[PDB]
Image (cartoon, rainbow, N blue to C red; front, top):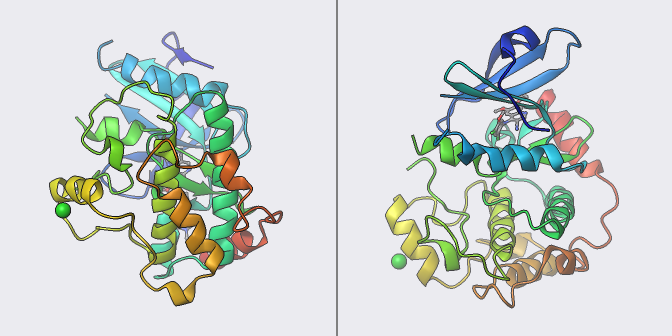
Length: 280
Ligand SMILES: COc1cc(Nc2c(C#N)cnc3cc(OCCCN4CCN(C)CC4)c(OC)cc23)c(Cl)cc1Cl
Ligand SMILES: [Cl-]
């Protein structure tokens, strides 16, 4: 549940390959030498270290099925190693790319439902995820999601990829955000944008340069689905309430769980069918 300075990671873990590409940085597939357990590993090279300690303490102290598990954190030579539960389905954005299509509404409903439960969990503990997007929603073969990353990939990219298309309007110009009573609501806006991304492959304003996107998010009316006819009234209403520019009136994850779009979702079937198809 923390970082081990007294251990060399190469005693525990063998590197067997690379996952994705893909800016944000190098992600390694690792295999435990004792157990055979698989991990995704990021290997990042005390003032550039306590940046990551908050994220590792989070991933350690979160016991929830829809959040990724920390399998090990090591500090050896100059590098910080973070070993995370391997999610064999990979990221949702990578799946949409493979199949050259967006998710169906039923599939989106499962992801949404599971993301809301995870965020309700995190927000009850005053943890804010800070980087929700399809790229940080990873999948199991059983058709569940795992919320990943928690900001780490963008902090590491800080040493047009990483443009914050998913960022809430109230914080789009901020490097660091104030502690306020509606700070966690920034995740809910990002959830909304992630749903549009899953519906359309790309988030709103994907065509624009990074600077222009900040301004566009700040100024524009909340984004809506490009082709409303394809989508239920529940989906559109859900987006409309989640994508509220005012963070005080924007609903919590608990409130959105009571919305018709997701309140009856009890099976992950649609997601299992999706992952089955991308394996084949
Ligand atoms: C360790 O650190 C981090 C790792 C991650 N990312 C990953 C975590 C985590 N966590 C877990 N598991 C992952 C699994 C992945 O792909 C495996 C499946 C490959 N495809 C299967 C389907 N076939 C057709 C094509 C290949 C993956 O791929 C890019 C990234 C993963 C992030 Cl997002 C942030 C941080 Cl900080
Ligand atoms: Cl603008």
